[PDB]
Amino acid sequence: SPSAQELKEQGNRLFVGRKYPEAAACYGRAITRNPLVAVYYTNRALCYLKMQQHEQALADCRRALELDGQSVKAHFFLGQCQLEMESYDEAIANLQRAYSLAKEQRLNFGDDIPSALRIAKKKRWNSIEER
Ligand SMILES: CN(c1nnc(-c2c[nH]c3c(F)c(F)c(F)c(F)c23)o1)[C@H](CCN1CCCC1)c1ccccn1
């Protein structure tokens, strides 16, 4: 009988091993034990994004944000999901929000957030210029 935290860690390990459906199933088992922990939904959202399930990834970002509105990771993954869905304005605003929250929380992700923002902004510009 694994605990919710053991299942979340098993999910993280499987994600690093590129076993995305198995990792998402582990996060689901963690949610069964404790459905009020935001990171179980944020981490499963990234599995759904890797599995090209954008609507499920969006839904899990929403569940995470209803539990932890200060989540840098929920905003970052939501922006990455929206970028793949071509919802450019929303993607940029969520990535900008992850940047501000990371700065307020003194979290260091190297250049990941500004790099993701430049990628999203360039994709938006090119899509508008080429219609
Ligand atoms: C990969 N990972 C992970 N946690 N945070 C990021 C991340 C990278 N860049 C970011 C970024 F720019 C942001 F703004 C932001 F908010 C972020 F959260 C991030 O990535 C974990 C595993 C963690 N591991 C163990 C200790 C270190 C590594 C995870 C996530 C989902 C599923 C499975 N596992």
Image (cartoon, rainbow, N blue to C red):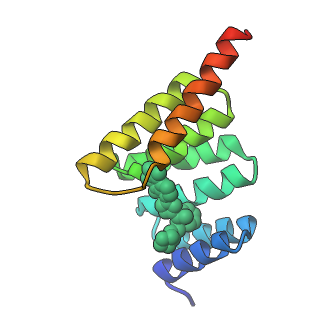
* Figure quadrant of the C terminus: top right
> Is any atom of residue 31 visible in this view?
no
Of residues 124 and 81, which is closer to you in this image?
A: 124
Please indicate, yes or no, whether residue 130 appears anywhere in the rendered image.
yes
Residue in the picture at 58% in, 68% down: 27
- Vertical order, 18 against 38 (above or below): below
Measured along the vertical axis of the image, is residue 63 above or below residue 95? below
Specify the quadrant of the image occupied by residue 93.
top left
Q: Quadrant of the N terminus?
A: bottom right
In percent of width and height, residue 113 lies at 46, 44
In percent of width and height, residue 16 lies at 64, 71
Residue in the picture at 26% in, 53% down = 105
Residue 85 screen position, x and y as percent: 68, 32
Q: Residue 42 appears at what percent x and percent y?
A: 51, 56
Instruction: Give the answer, above or below, for where 31 lies relative to 92.
Output: below
- From this view, report whether residue 123 is shown above or below residue 14: above
Rendered residue at 59%/34% (across/down): 119
Q: Residue at x 37, y 42 (%)?
A: 99
Q: Is residue 128 left or right of residue 112?
A: right
Q: Quadrant of residue 2?
A: bottom right
Horizontal side of 118 relative to 127 (left or right) equals left
In this rendering, would 115 be left or right of 37? right
